[PDB]
Image (cartoon, rainbow, N blue to C red; front, side, top):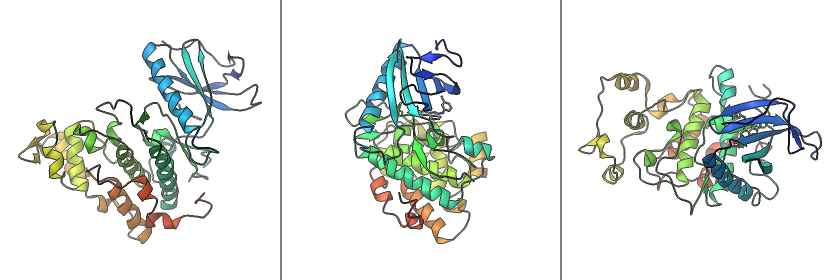
Length: 327
Ligand SMILES: O=C(O)c1ccc2c(c1)nc(Nc1cccc(Cl)c1)c1ccncc12
C-alpha cells in the first residue's frame, strides 16, 4: 500500500506536504518546502513501502548520485536530486520543483505542435542532456514527453528550458539488461525484435519525441508488436534484412517479409494514417528539412548505424539556434 499523508503533514521535520503533484504505479509525488533550504519548494517522490519498489528506488538513487557528481555545476539539464532518505521503508527523494511536462502542455494546447524554434531548442537540450548521460555508461530507458519537464511552463510556452526526469529505469553499462525496456510508443525495433539494446535506444525514442513535438501526436500510436513493425516499415522503409535473419521472434515474418492482414482493423488503420516520414513535414523551408533529416537518422532501424547524440549535436539543424539558446 501507500502512505499515511494529507496536506500540511510533516516529513523528517524538514518538509511539509502542501499538496499533491501526481500519483502513479510507484507511489506519490508531493509539493513541499524546506526548513534548512529555507522556504524552498521541492517535488518529493515517495516510493511505496513494498520490498521490490524500495530496492528499485535505491538503484535509481545510485543513478541520481552519479549524475550529481559528474554534472559538476549543473549544465546538463538532468533533474537534480536535492535530498534522499529512508523515511520508514518509504524511500523518498527531493527534486527541485518544476513546471509541467512536455505532454501535459501539449494536451492542454489540444495537441497542437510547438513551433520549429521551440522544437529545435528542446531537441538541442535533449541531445545534450542524454549525450552527457551516455558518456557516463548510462541509458535512460524511458524517454517520452511525460518525462521531460519545463523548468517553468508559463504560456506558446514562454521559456523552452527543459529537464529530463524519472531515472527509475536508467541502466548502467554493467547492469543486467532486461529484454524489453521502453514505453511501447518509444520502443526501438532492436528491442521489439529482442536483439539486445544499449544507448541507441534513447536516440530512437528521442526521434519519436521530436516528431510528437513538431506535429502534436505520437508517431507510433500502437499497441501490438506486429502493428508497430508495420507502422515502422510504412513510415521509414523496409526492415533491414540482416535484422530479420538475426531475430528470434520469427512469428512476425515469412520469407523475409512482415506477415500482415491488411484488411484487419489495424491494417486499415495503418493504411489510412501511416505515411512516409517526409510527407509529415509541414513546410518545405531549409530549417524543416534539416530537422527531418535529423529525425530520420535518429530513426535508423539498425542501432549500430543509428546516429549518436554526440553526432546529433554536429547537425546543421542546430545552426538555427539563439546564442542564449546555445547555453
Ligand atoms: O521521477 C522523477 O524523477 C520526477 C522528478 C521530478 C518531478 C516529477 C518526477 N514529476 C512531477 N510531476 C508529476 C506529474 C504527474 C504525476 C507524477 Cl507521479 C508526478 C514534478 C513536478 C514538479 N517538479 C518536479 C517533478
